[PDB]
Structure formats: C-alpha cells, structure tokens
Amino acid sequence: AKQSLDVSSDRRKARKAYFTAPSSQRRVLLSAPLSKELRAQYGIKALPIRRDDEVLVVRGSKKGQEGKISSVYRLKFAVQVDKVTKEKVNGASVPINLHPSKLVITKLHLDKDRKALIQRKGGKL
Amino acid sequence: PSRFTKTRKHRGHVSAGKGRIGKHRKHPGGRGMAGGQHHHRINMDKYHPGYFGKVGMRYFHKQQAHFWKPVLNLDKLWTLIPEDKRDQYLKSASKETAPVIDTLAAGYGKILGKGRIPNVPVIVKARFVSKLAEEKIRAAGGVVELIA
Amino acid sequence: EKAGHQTSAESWGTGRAVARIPRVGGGGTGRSGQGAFGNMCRGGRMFAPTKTWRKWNVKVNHNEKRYATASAIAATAVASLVLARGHRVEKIPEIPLVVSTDLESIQKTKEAVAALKAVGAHSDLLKVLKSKKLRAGKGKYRNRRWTQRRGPLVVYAEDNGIVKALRNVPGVETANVASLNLLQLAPGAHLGRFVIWTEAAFTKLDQVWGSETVASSKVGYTLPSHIISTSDVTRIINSSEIQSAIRPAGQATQKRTH
Amino acid sequence: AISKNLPILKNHFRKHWQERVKVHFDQAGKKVSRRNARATRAAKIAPRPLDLLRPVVRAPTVKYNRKVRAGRGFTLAEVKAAGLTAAYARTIGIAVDHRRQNRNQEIFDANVQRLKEYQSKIIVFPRNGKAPEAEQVLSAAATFPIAQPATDVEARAVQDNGESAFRTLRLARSEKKFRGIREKRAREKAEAE
RNA sequence: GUGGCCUAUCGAUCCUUUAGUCCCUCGGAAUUUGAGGCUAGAGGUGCCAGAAAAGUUACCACAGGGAUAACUGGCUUGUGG
RNA sequence: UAUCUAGCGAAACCACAGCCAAGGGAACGGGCUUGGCAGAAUCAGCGGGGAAAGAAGACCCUGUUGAGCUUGACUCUAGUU
RNA sequence: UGGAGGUCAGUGACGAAGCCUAGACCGUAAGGUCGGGUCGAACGGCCUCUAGUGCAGAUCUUGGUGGUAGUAGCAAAUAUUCAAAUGAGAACUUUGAAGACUGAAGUGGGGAAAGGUUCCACGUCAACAGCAGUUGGACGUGGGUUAGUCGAUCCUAAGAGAUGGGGAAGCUCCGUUUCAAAGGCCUGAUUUUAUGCAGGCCACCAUCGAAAGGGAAUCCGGUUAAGAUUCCGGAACCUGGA
RNA sequence: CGAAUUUGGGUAUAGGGGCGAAAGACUAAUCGAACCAUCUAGUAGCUGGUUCCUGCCGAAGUUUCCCUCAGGAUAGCAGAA
RNA sequence: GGACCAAGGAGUCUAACGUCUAUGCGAGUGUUUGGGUGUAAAACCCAUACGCGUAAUGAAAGUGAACGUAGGUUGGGGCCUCGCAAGAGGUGCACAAUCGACCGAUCCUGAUGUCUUCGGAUGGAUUUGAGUAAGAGCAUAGCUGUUGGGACCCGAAAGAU
RNA sequence: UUGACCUCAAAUCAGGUAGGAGUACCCGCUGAACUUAAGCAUAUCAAUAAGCGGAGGAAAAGAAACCAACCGGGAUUGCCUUAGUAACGGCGAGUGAAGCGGCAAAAGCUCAAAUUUGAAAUCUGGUACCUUCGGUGCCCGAGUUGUAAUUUGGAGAGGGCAACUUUGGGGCCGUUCCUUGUCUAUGUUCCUUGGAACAGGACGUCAUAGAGGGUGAGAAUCCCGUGUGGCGAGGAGUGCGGUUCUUUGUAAAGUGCCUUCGAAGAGUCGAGUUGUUUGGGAAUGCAGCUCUAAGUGGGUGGUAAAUUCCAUCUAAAGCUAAAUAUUGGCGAGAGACCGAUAGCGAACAAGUACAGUGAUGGAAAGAUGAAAAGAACUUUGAAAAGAGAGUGAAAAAGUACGUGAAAUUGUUGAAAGGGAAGGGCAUUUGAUCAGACAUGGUGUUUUGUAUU
C-alpha cells in the first residue's frame, strides 16, 4: 500500500539494491532485534549489529545458543559469533555465519556514538 | 483474438489454405492498382466504370466554406422549434403569434419543400429557399423572410 | 527495432552445399559462417516483430459502458449471483446490504474490521486472506507474485476516513457512488460483486442512475428497458390465459412403437 | 492487385512511414503534466486568474459568421471606449489586440460592456498598499462567458407582402450576373450619338 | 430509302483539332482578348481491348524448367535393312 | 607401399537398405507381381551395378532477371565548338 | 501451449514442476487421468481474456551424436645400432662406443624483414609435440639485453607535405616559392644595468622522407647459465668546451 | 642464364579507377569492374517449406480480355451465411 | 529433400475498407483532441465543435424531391368476418414484376411582365441519375476477404552512397 | 624638418576567443539507387538513406508586405478536423497541402531612417580604492565617416491650451525550489513435519503500515523498509509576507483638446530565362544569369493579358518564454513483454576472446550446497586415481557439481534372426495386468449385550 512515487515496489530493483548496497547500507540491513530485557531497559526495538554485542541465536539449528559477536561480514551479509562454529573432519573449527535477523541481542557494546544512537531512537539509557 | 483465426485451423495442413498448384506467391498480379488498363481492365470495367480519364472543369483553391449550405425540408422544419413549445404552437395556430424559425441558427442554408407541413402559419427565416418550399409555407399561411 | 539485424550477413548463394540463408562473414570467431536474418535462425529477427503501434486500448460506447454498469449494480442485489461469484454472504442478513453513515465517518482500521464483523462480511475478507496464494507462472518475476480473491466493495458518498480505514484490509475495495467502476462491480466479467452500500450511497444512487420520476443527471441518459416485461416465462407459459388456448399435450416421452 | 467488387482505397504507405509513427501513449501523462503546470503557474501568480480577458468576435467565413466566439484581444478603440490605455490594460489583465479593427457597432458595444464589467468585478492590489487577499478565481473565460446574442423573439406577427422570397433571390442573382453587360450596353448606347 | 443485295472492309484513356451551344467557369467586382468545360466528329495505336525501343556475348551471371532441345531407353517403322 | 601387429586415428557419403530373371510401372526395380531361390561371422582384391560421390546443368529454353561489350537503337551527358 | 481477469477460502517440502516407465483407465482422435521410480519449490481444474500458441521435412537454424571405423591412413628429404645412467615406465632422454649424412651457392658461423622472450637455469608431464616421451620452441617459477666510438639520431633521393595564396556548400583540393613586408649571422659598445646599442655583412624561402645510399670517432685479450666492438684489463681515437 | 637480366627496401598510381611487351590479364587464394559497411528484411509472375484432431460439404484445368502463353482479372465450378 | 536427435522455426500487426454477425442508441450517432476528477496511464463525468447519416443531380452556373389515402395493377405472410362440417370475402407489412407521379441533367415549347433581352410560367420528349415516393444510420467488437506496408517464411544475377 | 591623418603590418606585447566530442530530437546544404509502375525513360521510392556544416535544453517559427471576401479574423507552434479533399500525375502507378472551426499554450516587441548642438550627454581598457557576476575616481583610448537620451507605424515628433495620476536601490528574516539526514507500530508465544518454519494447527497484536525485498521453504507482526506525521543540514532566492536605512527629483512615465509634420530598409521589389522543387496547375518556393524600379508607392487577392476599381497587409533589418520534438546524457516509476538457442551482440574479466594489412567482422559462456561443512584418516597404485571412511537433509549434489531428456553407447536380462527390418487383420504361445465380494440384511445357532 505504498503511497509515494519515489518508492518502488519492483522486485528486480529491490533485489539489485540489496545485493549491491555498500557497507554503510549493509549495517542498517544487518540490524538485529533486542531481547525482551533489553527492550524493557532501553525502549528501543531493533538496532544495527556491532562487534562486541552479546547475541542469542534464536532460530535455526543452533536454537537458543549464546555468544559474543566475532565479526560482522557485511560482504557475506552475515555475523560470525564466538563459540558457534563447525568442527571439520580434519579437526579445525571454522566460523559458522548467521543472519542477525535470526538473532537476539542480549548485551550491547556501548560508547558515545551508540548511546547517542539509543537516545536518538528514543532510548532512555 | 488469434485463437479464433483460420491459421490456427490450418496448423497441420501443408499449404495453409493457399493451394498446391498456384501457391501463395508475392505479387502475381502487380502491386496496388497495377495493370488497370491491361490485365485488370475486366475488373475495372465491370466494377468501377468511369475510372480512367477526366471530365469537368478544374477549380484552383476551392474552399468548402463557400459551398457550406445544408438543406432543410419542410417535414423536418417543425423539429427546429423546441419540443415543449411545439404542441403549444400547433394548438395556437394563428397569425400575429406565429413562431419564427431561424434555420440559419439551426445550421441550415437552404429550405427545400419535401412537403406536407400543417396549415398553421409560421415564420421561416432562411437565407435560401426553394420555389416549392416558399409556395408551401405561403399556402400554410406563414411567410419566409430572407436573412444573411 | 534493430534486434536480429545488427549483422552484415550475406547469402553464400548456391553451389556450396549449404542452404541459401544469409550467413555472417569474416573468420576465426565461431560466429563466422553462421545463419542470420531469419526467424528460423538462432540470433535472427523474430517473425513479424511485435510493434509498439498495436492497438492496446479499445473504445466502448459510453451508453454501452453505462448499460453494463447498471447490470452489475442490479446483479449486486441478486442473492444467487453473489453466491455464484463466491462471496460468502450466507450469514449476511439480506442483500443489497446497507449501513449507516457512521461507517462513512469511520477512521481506524480496527473500527473498519469491527464494522465488517458486525455486518457479516468478515467471512468474505478472511476468505480473501486465506485465498492469498503464489502465482503459477512467469508473472511472479513481473511484479505479480501473489493472487487472492476479491472481497466486499464498500460504496460511500462522502470520504471521511473510509479509504484510509479500509485501505489495509485485504480484499476489501472502496468506491463512491459517483464513479462505480464496472471493473470492480463485475470483476472477471462475473456479475454479482458483494457490495456494502452506505445509506447516503443508496440515496445518491437513486439520483445518479435515474428512476421513473427523477432524471439520471447523466446528460441525455436513461436506464435501459428490457425486451421482456418479466423474468418468469414459466409463469407466463403456465398462466390461464396461455393455457386455455392451447391444444392438449402429448406425453413428454413418445412410446417406442414398432 | 485489383480484385473483387471493392472500393478503390488510397493508402499512402509506400514511404518509410514506420519510422515516422507517433503513438500517443503519453496522452494521460501529458494531461497530468498539463494540469500540474496549470496548478503550479496558478500558485506562482496566486491572486491572478491564470488567463487573460478575451473579446467577443464574429467568426469570419459564411459557414461560421452565424456564431460568436472568443477573440485574440480587445481593440485600441475598445480599450479607449472602456476608458483605459492599452499598456495599463495589458498590465492589469486584458488582452489587447492592436491589428483588429471594429467596423461593427454591436460588437463594439458588447466588447466595451465586457471591459466595463471586468473592471467592475476585478480588484487591483495597489503597488504599496496592504494587500487585501482576495480568493483567486482561476478562469476569466468561465467568469465572463461568451454568450451568443439573441436576434429576435420566439413568436412575432406574420407580415406577408407578396414576393415569395424566391423570385427576389433569383432576380438578385440575375442582376449580379448581368450588371456588367448592362453597364457596357449603356456605355455603347450613350457613346453612339 | 438511316449508304453499297447479305455475310469482311477496322480503333480506347491522355493530348491536339474542328463543329455546335455563343451555353457554363477563370472563385474580391467587371469589360475585352486568352484559357478551361459541356455534346459530336477527326489526327492511332495492324502486337489491331491500343508500351515510345537496336545488337552481341565462344568472358559471362541468376531464378527456374525434363512444361523444352542436344544421349540412352520407350511407342511407330515412313526411310534404311 | 599395400598386407599383419603395437600405438594413434580421420573423411566423403548415408530415406530405409542391399541376390537375381521376366512382367507391369514415370516406357531401364533393391523393394511391387510371378518365378529362381535362400544359412552365422568374415579377410584380401575388384571395379559390373548402386541410372555411386563431388556442384540448385555452365549446353538449351523460359523469365516482361542481369551484367561485359558494340552500334546509324531509344533517351541523355562530361568535354568541345 | 505461454501469459491475463475471476473462481475453486484448489494441489503442494508429509513432496509442486520436470523427467523415465512393452503398468492401469478414459476419449474415434487431438489428448486427459492415475500407479511405480527420480526430483526439490512451485503448480493446476472451471468461466472468460490474450498470443511471439502445436513441426518430420524447408541442401531449415544452433548444438549434440552416429554408421562408415579401429577403417583410410601416420610410406618424399639414404639410417640406424650396442651398452650404461636416469626413471614406475625408454625405439625416441643423457653419456660413451660404433655406422652415417649435410660436404664450405652446408643440415656450418652470422645477420635484414618478421616474431616477441621462443634466449638461459631450475622444477615438472595433465593438455600439446597426428607413436612415445623421464625430452621440448610445451607447463610453472625466475634470471638475462650495459656503448662517446655499432645503429638510430644528422643529410638529402624518388617523393610526402604545412605556410602565403587561390578553389570548393563543405569534408577538404591545389600549390612548395609561388603575384608574401617571409629571418638568422658575427666582433665589440654603456660596461653605477639590460647584450634596447652613434656596428656591420647579409637574404639562400618550412618540414618529413634511407637501421642497404651519404656519414666524426675502438681495437685486442678475458669474462656469463644466458650480454658484450657495449662489461673487465690494456691500449687508442673523435666531437664539443675550457 | 651478362642482360629488354634477377632482386631487397623506399616511393607513385585506387575501383568504371589504376596498371597492362595486351591474356580481359593483374589490382592481398577476390576481377568481363576489388574489398568493407549501409541503403536492404532490395524485387522475384520462379524453386523449397508452411506445425493439432474429428465432423459436414466439396472442385478446376473451361469462357472472354491482358507484351497474354510457368502469371493475372473475369464468368463458371465450391463453401458459408 | 531427408544419416540421426533435442531446442528454435513460417499468413503477423497496422492504416483505410467490402460482406456478414453481436451489442448500444436511433434521425440521429460517436465521452476518451481537450476539460473535470481520481484510490492516478485505470475508472467516473462534461461540452461546443468535428466526422458519418438525414438530398439528389449537374462539368458548372445552378436547381432541388406528394393530382392521388405517398398512386394504379399482379402476387403476397399475417390478421379480420363467415361455415360444428364447403370454402369465400375484406385488409394486406416486407418483398418481387409492371404502369405511373415527383426532383436533377439533356433536348424542345416559350405566359403575364419586361433596368427590351432579362425572366421562365405552362406544356412536352423511343433521353439520362449512384435520386423521392412515412427515413436507417452511427459507433464498438468478431470471423472472412482487399489494398499499401519487410507482409506467410528463406532465396538472386544486380543497382546506389 | 613641431607632429598628425589614412591604409597596411610586426611583436612569446595586455586580455580574450574559435577549433574537437556527443549528435536521439533541431537548423541548413548536398543527395542516390534498390523499389513501384506487373517491362521502362517522366513519375515513384524521396525533397529519403549515405556525405557535409551548425545549435540547444529544446531548436526552429514568431508578432503579418498574414488569412480572408465574412456581420470579417488577428504573432508563432502543436493536437482533433479540414482530407485522402482542392490540386498535381506516361491524369497511369501514384501523390497531395491550406483557410475557416474546436482545443493546448498564449506575450510581446526594437533598430535604421530626426540637430544634444546651450556643450559625446556614450563606451573598452590601464591605474587606485571598495562592500568584487560588480561600484566609484583619474588617465590614455574608441568615437562626430556618430557612441548616449527620444521615436518604430499599434504609431510617433514639434509647438500651444489644460486639471491631474503613478514611481527608488541594495541587504535580512521567512515563504518557495534543488539536494540531503534523522526519528516515527504490531508474536518470532505453544503443538506437528522438516536440515532449516518463512509450512500446517491454536491463541493473539498493529494497521493512515496486508507495497517490495532479505532471512536455511509461501513471513503485515524477525530485519530493512512500507504508511502517517515530526525534527535537522547545504545552496539558489525578488514568485511574494514582513523589515533595514536610503528623498530624492521644480527627476521619470501615462492620459484630454488643437495646429504643423509624420523620415519607414535597392543590384531590392519586380520582369525575363535557366535548373530544381511544390498539391501550386501560362510557372509554389529556392538558386544562377540578364534587365532592373517607385512613393496615395509596393506586395498579395491560386488562369496568362490590357483597362477600371475594391479589400487587406507594409518586404528587401532585429529580439522573444509556453504549448511542441527527443531510439543520445543523467535521475526515476512501471509492463497481460522475454526468460540464458529467448531478451540488446553482450544476464558472465562483451564490443571481450578471436579473424582480417585495412575498413571492419565478432562469439561461446548463468544455477553445488542453507552453510565448503570442498571429503580428515586407512589401504592399493609411481602417479592420476580407486576401494573404504567422512561432511551433508541429499554425494541419485564432489567443482568434469540444481534436475539431467533424446540421438548415440556399455553391461545385464528376455526374445527373434536361411539375401533387410518395420506394419494391418486374426488366433496361439510366453510374460505381465485391471476389473464383481464380504455391501441394507427379512436368517438372528451371538463378542467389547444396537458394537457383526
């Protein structure tokens, strides 16, 4: 039910924009939701994901598994969390990447910019 | 709709309804009106006599606005006045109150006498009138005054 | 317009044991010596290429459009036609269904759904909801991914929040009496769209379409008249007037003699 | 080429007509663009009526001289009679046409009355006043419609005096046809003693 | 008696020309030349329902034809034997 | 060289195929009719046949298809006078 | 058969579409339905709308694949052999021993055009070298071309071609000293400066065009895996300047 | 086989043009008019092909005219309404 | 022509039209150049104009369609009156044949009047029109057929810049 | 010889400017033939393609030497119509406009020809300063062979009479435009299948948001967005609402009456002829050549000419937005379009690889999986690899990767086979296979007693 003329409901254009978006846009794309307690504490629903954010995998075969973010792969549209890996048959552990929309942020990595972002989005600190 | 055409029904048969002996070639008789004097003269003479040649005078820079002159007949004359007033005028058919009909305002140039208007009087403002039309209006008791 | 023709191909002629189709020249490419310029050829121009001046819109007589619109409006009231179009109006009290102008002034989608519940068309709108389904062709990647049924057509006189309130309700369409599209009064050319009028909509309809005592406010327009005075030719046939003048009947199945 | 009983059709399509084909897909978009242009121009000239005042004019040829339509602009005689100069008329919204001549008393009167009522209805804001915002109307043409002048009453008395209105037409045509011959004959009869 | 005792002895469009109406038109209005029309003949297409038209190719080309010639075969057998 | 072997390994052509005699038949059949007949798988040769393969016959004719050349053909033209 | 409006609140990851199936049913048929296997994300019935809508052919187009067929063939340039080493493997690589050939208008030693790194070393054999390959002008990784004296650069040849001019609608054409006011040489002067100069001789009318023509000057010995008239040692020469 | 010799490089001549000790020869495997792109999907009365099923009806190769004779128009024969 | 297989592959769209058919309105018809509006190329609405039709005929100037119940005659479906049972009579739409009448063109005749050679009444004629004689058209759509377009698909030898 | 002037040059003099590209549309020049005419030469194709010159965001045209003949319209452009018409045309094939009308948009104007003559009032440049798209001083210079003011035919100028009416410049907040930023709801609750829930089922929530996309399968409510509003930033800014100082200026402009005037474009109009073009026909426009004007003159009034008039404009000079065009450029939104032999030649390191001396020609080529988790390890082999193992939901996904058809092939199995094979009708033989139960139950000898 879009009403603007500059908003396009074109599947091809939307997919092209998603796959071609640069890192600045991939951050907003890889926004992740907050936990019930974090939503209660801040008043803010979802946030772009960062590096030292504590997250809870809450969907998929790693359901209900906690961990600290190791690296957000903006190029691969994924987040690699500490201690959620796969054990190869040769005995090496490889990071398993997962999408932040299937996540719940349990603890944030705060700084001046993140606090200003919470305040600007309506959070109370 | 393409699904209704006979090409869909010819799908399967070799020649597509165009014959095996005389195929569908490109232009076996010529293009357009070719050969109207030579090998289509029979069609030209049977179906379009008078085609070839010229008869009348010429007219350089002919204007159709000069010859604009739609014709109104007497039978259609009474339809120029408004319908609700028509019964009124017919019943009050008399002089000194006759309706004036502006055929030129209605969009007609000449009045022709196709005949049998009622014997009420009526004022016919025209710019051209036929002899019989004026005669029939006068017989009905009206008059035609010429306008421009 | 230049598709299939951006080649300099020339026919090899005869005497080279190959068909006489045009072939591209040059060498060392793999494309060289290959057929061109034909509907039968890979990379050639399509037979009778589609042209932009094909007729797209079709003129229809204004009076014929209005005739069809009046038929669709009339079919709205017929209970059997709405069922045949499949509009889940069985638990509706009666059709043509009419509501107060409080609907006309409704402002929220919650209130719109509540009014729909009250009048009994929620069954139709949740039919639309459960009928949402994925398309069955290449129309999916042409911005037509999903299909769903049509719901009720709420028809109003004044817009005081109707289009906004019922904008997000799936299937439910809104229109005002002045326009009353045939495209929504008979979707798919099937008569009997389920219509929820407002009281102002009915009162305006009587004047917009004219009656036996009021002109239709469409200039020079009048509602079409039937070629038959009634719809029960069975009643006409079995009336005593018709039945008293007819010879005795047969038996509805002739005995198979010999 | 030529075939069964059919009309001769003259289809002028043996140039490269396919290169010069204009299909008016932009009819709706152009209509929207025109309405947008009218809206934005009206907003730009916000108190002004978005068009100029046109005169009443009689359509030229013998096919159309029965109708009265809009002109291009009021004559200099018409603006002088209305009591204002052409330059000021142009500034305050009257179309002034310099090359139109009025030989007609009733077209003169109709246009002067048009101008007088236009001056009566519009209000001009002073250059350095207090700007009495005045609820712009957007069409001088609709505000001052062109009305076809009525000629005579619907019902009047019948006056017959016996000319049939056909003999007069015939005799007028004949006099036009033979005027020069009769003038020449009069010249020869006068010059021969 | 509406040409030759009968059955053959002949000719479109366009153009030109002549005869007649001295009629219609030259379109801002007239006169006089001039031109254009109306009706009937004439100037001719004999390839005669009516293109304005010289060769050569053994340097040759293309679309076709076994509707069509140069071999065999087939029928015939004048001619030959 | 061919031939046999190890290695390597194409192409032309191919409706389907592959024994004859006579008949009839598009008047010269591998197939049809009537007869003769008829036994797996094959190798080297061979040039009778496959009207064998090569190429939309180059001869010939037709086309209101060309081109090279010629001329007192038709219609023009550079140049020159 | 592809797509579109409506409808079956249709089928479907508990398996849609597709495909295989001398399994079943239906229809005269076009075809439709179903069983079994494979597969993994969409698809269908009915009423209508629409078309780039149905293939056996077109010496059809593109791609793929056959029989022929393990067949024709791999037969010009006299020609190879023994042993050892290497290696999984040797007719073909390496070394030695033989036997030969080109036979100084050579199968030798250099170059021009062209190529472009093929040169050289190390490693290596999937593909290529119409057999093979441990070999290679192949593949991978690198290394390598050193000038005052060799050549270009300079000159002009046939010729090409701006300028001044003329033509051409114009792209551009002619023209090369023409019907142009066409410049660059040589010592010092004031030497509180600039080379503005009481200085003077002059006028040839661009430029490009040769790695074989003309032309300033380098030789020997040694040296590298691969450069040498170029590096090194020695011994000279030419031009320009001071 | 000492010259009307052979030849490298530079240079000139460009398509109705060049060049030819002359063969219509040569002008990049292209010459009785090169090659490239475009006009151009050039035109073809001439070859070839022309894609599902069933049901009902069902021919013509003749007339007249045509630079007409491998083609058309016309009438006929045929279907449909 | 076809070695073989798969995929592609050939009467299309458009501008003007003919016949037929369906629909709407009907002496009218056609909104969609444009304006208004809009949930925005949609739908809905509006108006002059314009096109075709309602008048033809003539080269043109020009003129321009009812003695009659819009005519007589033949034939006509249906209807009406009659006969329980024969069959007859009246009225007869469409349509067909025929004889007329009307309008225009052609050839003649030539009234009162005369801007004295204009006017053209009246009466005709083995002549002639794609006409009148109680309108039928306009618009949209469908098959089929036509023409120009690359024109069902592929195909020259050529010609030009 | 005190020095000018004119004309012509030179400077690496001071400051500028032009060239080339792109070229869809626009303005011109130049200019075919194929084709059609069933042949072909005029004609047509076509005032087209190709070639050349020149612009812009539009270009061009444009305020009548117009159209008309009317009761007259009134710059240009474009649309509907006029109209396949008037007309041209081997009058054949064919071609073919315009006036009026209805609309879209509308906007008007300025130079030459006049003595400022009581004052060249004008302007470039150098230098200086300043508030620098410029302003102000001085100085050369240009210019009287004419730069300012005033006038442009609609008029206008000069001189008199006569009340009057109207003005101003540059900033600043804002509005407005372009660009851009940020904020602004609702479940991932329970059950089943699954590798994954985004599927099904239960219960909800938001909706001015149920458009679209992503996420391990069809997700309004998981994410980005979507909808509705709000709050910021950078420039343009007389379209205008306020405000700043700025009185200047017996300055500028308009109107009433009368008088005298009233300049208006020349190798040009026009005529002849030639070529081309047009629907333009005794000649529509254009161009060459020859002749070559006038001032109630000149042009036009679609049949050549001579005689009267009449009507309508006022050339040989110039500017000008909008409606209109736009297969190019940039930014966007869409589709009853195509779906990897399709759609652009190119969905990919595509104008790429490659070919040709050159002009030019010009492909093929998309898909593992949700995630490389891309196969550790063992054994055989010289290796490539195989056999096990392993990951994965699947290895019937192993990079030679989605599915994996046909031609063609191997193996196995079945059957047949004396110079083809295949087919129709009919049966036999072998193989293989579908189709009727027990269903209501009058009999009830019987269980979980209305459960067969």
Image (cartoon, coloured by chain):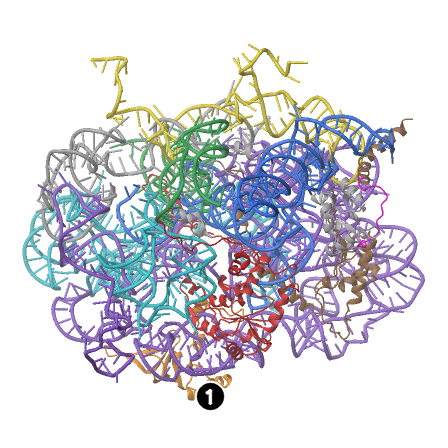
Chain colours: A orange, C red, D brown, E yellow, G cyan, H green, I blue, J purple
User: Could you say which is closer to the camera, residue J307 or residue G9?
Assistant: G9
Looking at the image, which is closer to me, C4 or I124?
Answer: I124
Q: Taking C52 as reference, is G39 left or right?
A: left
Q: In which quarter of the view is residue G121 placed?
A: bottom left
As helix, strand or loop, the secondary structure at mark 1 comes to: helix
Q: Where is residue C231 in the image (x, y as percent from the top left)?
A: 53, 61
Relative to I82, residue I60 above or below: above
User: Relative to H35, does residue J322 appear above or below in the rendering?
Assistant: below
Question: Would residue D152 be counted in the magenta stretch?
Answer: yes
Task: Please provide percent x and percent y for residue J326.
Answer: 55, 56
Q: Would residue B47 be visible to someone looking at this image?
A: yes
Q: Within the image, what quadrant is residue A81 found in?
A: bottom left
Against A51, residue J314 (above or below) is above
Q: Can residue A52 be seen in this view?
A: no
Give the quadrant of residue C179.
bottom right
Residue drawn at (40%, 64%) of the image:
C136
Point out residue D60 in the picture as x, y percentages from the top left corner: 75, 49
Residue at 23 percent across and 77 percent down: it is A90
Residue at mark 1: A42
Query: Chain for mark 1?
Result: A
Question: What amino acid is labelled 1 in the image?
Answer: Tyr
Please give the name of the residue rendered at 46% of the width and 36% of the height, measured from the top-left corner. B28
Highlighted range, magenta? D151-166
The one of G20 and G145 positioned closer to us in this rendering? G20
Residue J97 falls left or right of residue A21 = right
Main SS of residues in magenta = loop
